[PDB]
Length: 10
Image (cartoon, rainbow, N blue to C red):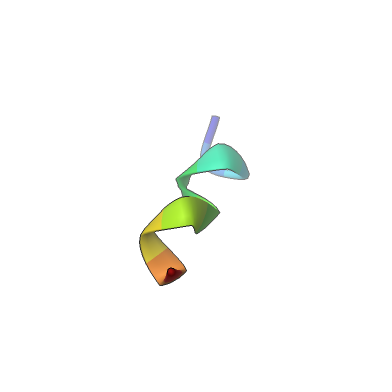
């Protein structure tokens, strides 16, 4: 999900 895409913030 887009919530898991948060890893891109890292």
